[PDB]
Image: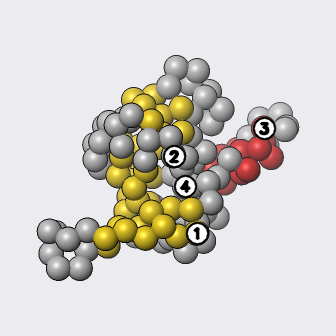
Amino acid sequence: SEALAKLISLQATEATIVTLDSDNILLSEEQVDVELVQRGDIIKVVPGGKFPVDGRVIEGHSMVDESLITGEAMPVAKKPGSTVIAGSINQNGSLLICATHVGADTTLSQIVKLVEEAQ
């Protein structure tokens, strides 16, 4: 019943958008607030960075600490063709995430509908 509130507090505040402007040869980055990224953008995550939303992974191989969110006390390894959740912690392997939900629309907000009836 305390976790049910804390789930939403774990969301990170900013995200890195990456934009191409010549061909696939040019890459340029913007850090933005979590309200300004959309569910059609692709986002960078760095060593030690936290997740603001859920999504699917399509570059890299980091180990992610999700021990509150999913309960895994043994941190989860990722790959291209993998999945992640908001409020988990990234390290060593640097990933690219395509966003399919926003800060309101997140599966993290979907879980707290289900975790209410768990008590």
State the mark number for residue 53.
4
- Residue on which the image places disc 3: 3
Q: Indicate the secondary structure of the residue bearing disc 4.
A: loop
Q: Is 54 located above or below residue 41 in the figure?
A: above
The amino acid type, in three-letter code, at marker 2 is Gly
Q: Residues within 10 Å of mark 1 (few under 14, many from 20)?
A: few
Return the x and y of residue 96 as percentages of the image width and height.
35, 52
- Residue on which the image places disc 1: 33
| Distance in Å between CA atoms under marks 3 and 1 | 25 Å
Q: Are marks 2 and 1 in contact (CB under 8 Å)?
A: no
Q: Are marks 4 and 1 in contact (CB under 8 Å)?
A: no
Q: Nearer the viewer, residue 84 or 95?
A: 95
- Residue on which the image places disc 2: 49
Residue 82, located in which quarter of the rendered image?
top left
Residue appearing at x 14%, y 68% in the figure = 25
Residue 76 in the figure: left or right of residue 60? right
Q: Indicate the secondary structure of the residue bearing disc 3.
A: helix
